[PDB]
Image 1 (cartoon, rainbow over the protein chains, first blue to last red):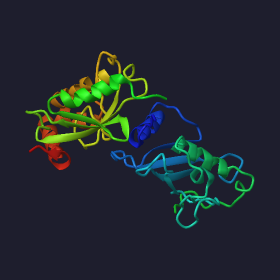
Image 2: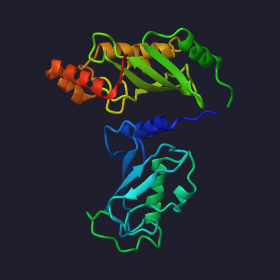
Image 3: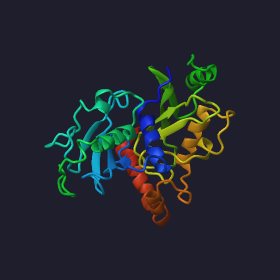
Image 4: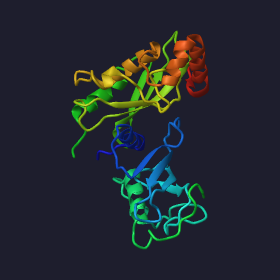
Amino acid sequence: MSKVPRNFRLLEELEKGEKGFGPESCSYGLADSDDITMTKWNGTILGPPHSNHENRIYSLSIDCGPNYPDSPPKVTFISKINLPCVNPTTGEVQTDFHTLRDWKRAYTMETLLLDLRKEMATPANKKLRQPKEGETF
Amino acid sequence: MASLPKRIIKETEKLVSDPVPGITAEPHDDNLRYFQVTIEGPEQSPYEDGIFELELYLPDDYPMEAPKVRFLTKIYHPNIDRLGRICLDVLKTNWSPALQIRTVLLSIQALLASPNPNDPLANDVAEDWIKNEQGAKAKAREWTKLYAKKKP
């Protein structure tokens, strides 16, 4: 019926950050400030407290392809992390991760970053050993 | 939640039957609120040799809410940013349901003809326009050649 196309959906996501809205714990913008297609995005997750992620930040690349948001983006950590849904040699978030596996058009990059941060904060994950800050995949 | 408003249907038809000069606008076959647009660079401007691609979208509350529009062609202009976003009063503070899609497109066309670096969107481009106007205009003409479709 009434579908906002890819490019204007991406503009909506961009302008939400530019207006100061969004969660405190993660953020995202363009990886290339002059990418008119707005394919490659860059995200930041603040590590959850009381965990081996505390006071750490994680940088990620998010690739919003031509069928986004009907299809999920592709997500690759830049910052090295020990997290079961993150492939340990490529940093790619595995497609069986629930947000991607069950991706719905309503989901945004915000949804995805918040779900990743929640995954970091589970009892089983918060105690994993982490690599040195500054290491990248 | 319904069929396309008649207001939009008629505007769409008239954009073809009674086109505005140097401008084309037609919806995507699979999304009738989403328009492919072209605007010719105005004569006697740095853009004059090019045809520029734009895209426009009609929000659900149109015409009470303004269309959304931006350039897909990369363009060097103080009031157009590196994503193609346009700083236009008619799209914000001066929008009215008395205006039309063709109003917006004409207003973009006139903006190409009268850049305003003193109220800028791309501050880097505006700075160049202010400190080296002839150099900035040359760069806009170069980018027209590099990125815009060539007029016949």
